[PDB]
Image (cartoon, rainbow, N blue to C red):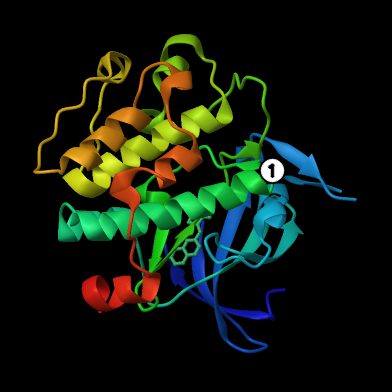
Amino acid sequence: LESQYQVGPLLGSSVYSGIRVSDNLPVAIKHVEKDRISDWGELPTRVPMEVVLLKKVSSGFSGVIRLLDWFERPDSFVLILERPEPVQDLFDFITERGALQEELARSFFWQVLEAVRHCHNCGVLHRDIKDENILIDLNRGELKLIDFGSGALLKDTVYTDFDGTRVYSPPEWIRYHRYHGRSAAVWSLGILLYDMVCGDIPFEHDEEIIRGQVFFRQRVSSECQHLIRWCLALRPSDRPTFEEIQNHPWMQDVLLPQETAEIHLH
Ligand SMILES: O=C1N=C(NCc2cccs2)S/C1=C\c1ccc2ncccc2c1
């Protein structure tokens, strides 16, 4: 209730810092307006799809933000989420530090891949993978995926709706308003990896997306450029599977998260 959490300041769009009074566990308190909800689901009881998806993934593995509880109110739902502390999102981290060293981008990108695999494996498609939806636990060197608000149940048939981020959306979406979950996710991941290693996204305009040429603006190793170009293949079915990505040579010898924090974060 109002009395089971103390409640601090806004964190962003919706979303306050809080301390669970049972044990002052740090938490994040997210408010979503019923009028602003696109997709709904049920439990055993009508809820935002977001809550369905979160319950399906909120099961131990720390690559995804865990939903600890939720409430319904007259015109909103309120979601109690886990909150690491100290923390920073990948968009701010990149904005400050600039392009990441390959070693660090490798550790981060690997952790993202583990977390997306987990979602898919729990039957959930995120649909908005990007720097702003990735939190860094700066002490442990661990990344967490957030914001399942554009997500969907994973399926093998074609999606004809998207409401994620356009500049991370694939060309098939842009030209046909059709995509398949996995292959579009792989594309978003190619966008994200370019961002990590170049300090910014590679395409701003629809036509750049559709054209698919990748220009590297920073020094990036040949293997990393190849992986990126691969994830950004124009034909969906020419993109790598999660497994091919993780067996790519650029992905070998990844640091553990703790090592990652000691070398690059502390
Ligand atoms: O799930 C999340 N969605 C976020 N932003 C978009 C919206 C907010 C309200 C309606 S739509 S932020 C977020 C989760 C989250 C979880 C833990 C955090 N800890 C520290 C800082 C930010 C955090 C955000």
Q: Give the residue number, with chain letter if any, for mark 1.
A: 123
**Which x, y percent locates residue 236?**
46, 20
Left or right for 233, reference 61: left
Q: Position of residue 165 (x, y in %)?
A: 42, 34
Vertical comparison of 158 with 245: above or below: above
Badge 1, how many Cα within 10 Å: few under 14, some, many 20+?
A: some
Q: Tag 1: residue type?
A: Gly
Q: Residue at x 52, y 61 (%)?
A: 63
User: Which residue lies at the image location 26% right of the left edge and 73% below the top edge?
Assistant: 265
Residue extending furthest bottom? 23
| Front-lying residue, 226 or 47 | 226
Residue 121 in the image: above or below residue 214: below
| Label 1 within 8 A of ligand 1 by Cβ | no
Location of residue 35 by image quarter: top right
Q: Residue at x 66, y 61 (%)?
A: 58
Q: Quadrant of residue 160?
A: top right
Q: In the image, is residue 266 above or below residue 225?
A: below
Quadrant in which the C terminus is drawn: bottom left
Residue 62 relative to residue 130: left or right: right
Residue 137 visible to the viewer: yes
Camera-side residue of 146 and 198: 198
Instruction: Please identify the residue farthest to the top as the structure is shown.
Output: 176
Q: Give residue 16's position: percent from left, percent from top.
A: 50, 67
In this orientation, does residue 199 appear?
A: no
Q: Residue drawn 42% across and 64% down?
A: 11
Q: Secondary structure at mark 1?
A: loop
